[PDB]
Image 1 (spheres, each protein chain N blue to C red):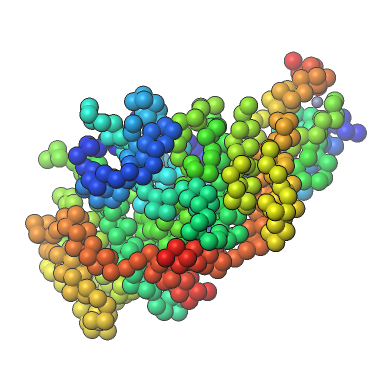
Image 2: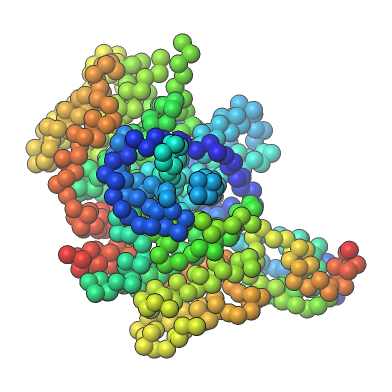
Amino acid sequence: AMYSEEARLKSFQNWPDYAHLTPRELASAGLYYTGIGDQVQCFCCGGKLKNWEPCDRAWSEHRRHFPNCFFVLGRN
Amino acid sequence: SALPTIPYHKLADLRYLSRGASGTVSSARHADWRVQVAVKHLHIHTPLLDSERKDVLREAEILHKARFSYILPILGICNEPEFLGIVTEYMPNGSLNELLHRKTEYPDVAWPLRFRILHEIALGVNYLHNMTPPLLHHDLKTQNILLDNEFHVKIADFGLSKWRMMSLTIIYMPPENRASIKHDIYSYAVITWEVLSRKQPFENPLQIMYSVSQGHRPVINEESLPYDIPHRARMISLIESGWAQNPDERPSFLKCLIELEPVLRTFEEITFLEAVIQLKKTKL
Amino acid sequence: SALPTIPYHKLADLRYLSRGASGTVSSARHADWRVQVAVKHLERKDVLREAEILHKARFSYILPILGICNEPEFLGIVTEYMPNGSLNELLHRKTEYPDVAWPLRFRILHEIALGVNYLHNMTPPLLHHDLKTQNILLDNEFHVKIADFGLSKWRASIKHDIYSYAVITWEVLSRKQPRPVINEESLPYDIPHRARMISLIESGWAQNPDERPSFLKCLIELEPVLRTFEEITFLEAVIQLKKTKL
Ligand SMILES: [Zn+2]
């Protein structure tokens, strides 16, 4: 079910209002929300991302940190 | 020479404060920076006419061009297609408008700080005329002057300020009504009298037009002008020179600063720190 | 660019304040304003770039620039003053400074965290690489201002600055010149929420940059600590300090 974007969107519930990235942008980036804090992860690697950079986009930071993504490989 | 903009999605928690001439004052907590940040806005989600767009644009530009440590800095603007608002820093303690006009909240305010903030505002306004061509604020009042946590005072609301060119409340007008630099001196004198006195001038406003212009001034009475405050006559002279009928004799801000300096030589910073407590606890 | 230019003849009371890495800071009273501005001079291009940077980033937690002194005999940058000096005088000198309260140091840490958060939250962001306790500036009431942008490079990113914030945190909770050990003698157990601070300091100077804290997370986890205190101690510890000075 995690493949469906609606699953990521519904996992993005109770997202704090101070986050710099809208749930939709993360869902397009292929990430989901665990429910605890601001922890997010991609379905390809499972790598958990934190310490949000306000100016960095989710796609850019996923590419930089984990260039081994199958999702990014298909994207590229 | 660039002023960064602020998207509306970053800013959060719009809180109403007041409605000014150049906008509607509001406070907010900037979510991305985790800073409480105040704002002002003529309109909310209305077709943005080009006149007010140019007004706020030039306001932001003039605020960014000349910034002083004694004036409130500017953070940015939101160039939204439907909403216009100035994003400026929030000094937590606020302004002097309610500070000087709330007897229940502030029954007494110590004269050391009452005169030290005068030194700060004098320094700010004196700098404000040092940059060529001299700037005429045109709207310097008790509202515009605002204080941070430690009561360090900054001025804002430059919206109707008009730069001086050489190509030759309605009760706040000087007897001048040609832009004259001495209007700043007149505003400084009236706010100096308002600081210690804690009394609002003009307390029908129609007679003020023919009164202040001709020479009438707010009443001088012993209850609002007691001799207990030291250097009372000096500040009487300062204000009476400040709001003179015409610009020929009003002293330059350097002269007022020099005159006030011996008054402020009668204090120590320890006295200021002791006196902030009484004001900070009487407003509780 | 677009900054005021003033002549050197508008300065009086030339008094030494400090010698900065990017240029000395002179406590010089103005003439038209007559205030002891912090004129910066000795490099001419370096200080012009410095003035450009300070004009670029303008926050209450950074000392506002006030102009430049474009004169052939001497080039200077005008900022506000520091009556009580930097944090070095407050902490490294304890012979006559008897004690510094916990609320003061915690407020200093919160201010530094916020300042470098914005410094990393610009378009495009900025990196400091010159954040030290001597560089931190205390105003008339010990509010934090940040100066000496000489090592600040326009833009390893978000690592040196957060490491500097962590080491300065441990410094101002320890008052000891500097990996630093976090034992009870250096960090006594009387400090409220001590274990939180220990976790913070080990996280901040972590060897691996991947787990290195971001300033945003720093401020969002530190906010309850400053929420615990009140304004009364904030405004009274400074009074106690000044009274102990005399
Ligand atoms: Zn991945």
